[PDB]
Image 1 (cartoon, rainbow over the protein chains, first blue to last red):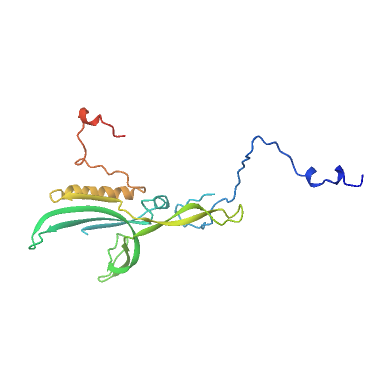
Image 2 (spheres, rainbow over the protein chains, first blue to last red):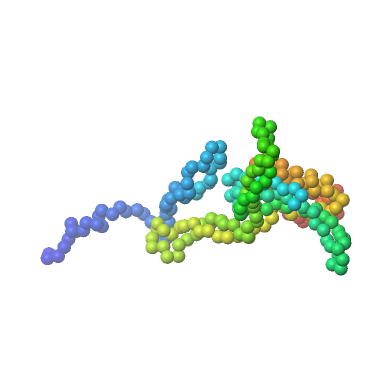
Length: 52
Length: 171
C-alpha cells in the first residue's frame, strides 16, 4: 500500500458524536442576561424592569 | 380649567401603553355652545379629562406654605408647565436584517404611537355635583398608587332585571 490508512484520520475521531432523531435538529441559546439600562434608582423608588 | 391636578406615577404605571409618560394631569372645565348669529349661550356642560403630559417650560406662581413652613408677604415659587404630546416612544423586540451571525440578530427597536385621553366624560349643566364627585374619584384612584380602574356611571347603564333584553350575547 502506497496510500494513507485509518491512523491518518484525526478530526473525525475527535469530534463528539450524538444521535439524531430527525432531519431537523433544534437547540436553544442564551445570549444576554438583560438590557444595559442603568442600575441606580434613588431612595424608595421602584426600579425599572428588564428582560433577557 | 376650573380644577387641575398633577400626579407623578411610578415605574409600573409608566410601563403601560396608556401611561407612556411619567406625569398625569386631571382637569375639569366648562364648555359653552354659542349662537352663531349673536352672542347668546344655548347649552352648557362640564367635561372631565385626563392626559399624560410632558414638561415644556416653567412659570412663577404664588407660594402657599404648609404647617411647618412660613412664607413672606410676597414670596413666589417656580413650577413647571405641561402640555399634551403628539406621540410617545415604546421599546419592542426586533431582528437585524443584515446580521452577520448569531450574536447580532435579536435587538430592540423604538416606535412612536398615538396618545389618547385616559378619561373623557361629559356632564350636563344641572349635574355639577356628579362631575365633582367623578373628578374626586379619579384623583383618589390616581393617589392610591395604581392605574385608573373604575369608570362606572349609573346614568348610562342599561336596565337591570330585564331578562328579555339582557339574555342576548354580550361576552
